[PDB]
Image (cartoon, rainbow, N blue to C red):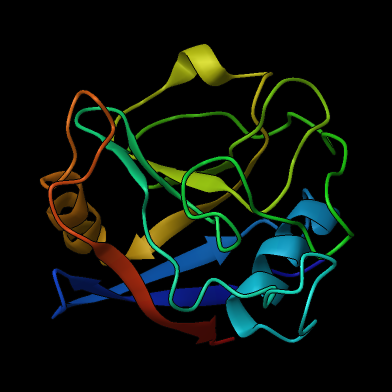
Length: 172
């Protein structure tokens, strides 16, 4: 199909830090892009977990310098939770798009066919993830805000400060 545009308004340690605008690849990975889009708008409401199927208020719980920022765990907030709009986990749709550089938007997973709601924004080219994580979008504005979050990561993945998706939604 077409390409949806979505956003995150970010706070870092409670301070407004700008907006990340993303373009999704609806034409390439419609099922995967659709999940992400609906989790930006919150339009499928409460999920099987009893929590909102919505990125609003969740955090980037895992941030590794010179790698990527990862979020989407709005049920456990620690990497162990999350849920797609489809009901818990769904299969890898395709591997058409590759990890080419900073700004790349890709799904976190725990092995083949385990996509949920967790995702990462790459801060480098992560070509070693090609064929293992499904790429479904890219940042088109606010890459500076991605760098600001990145500066709060650690090798250990633990953030030094709460990096929060304070608002989010669909644009066009």
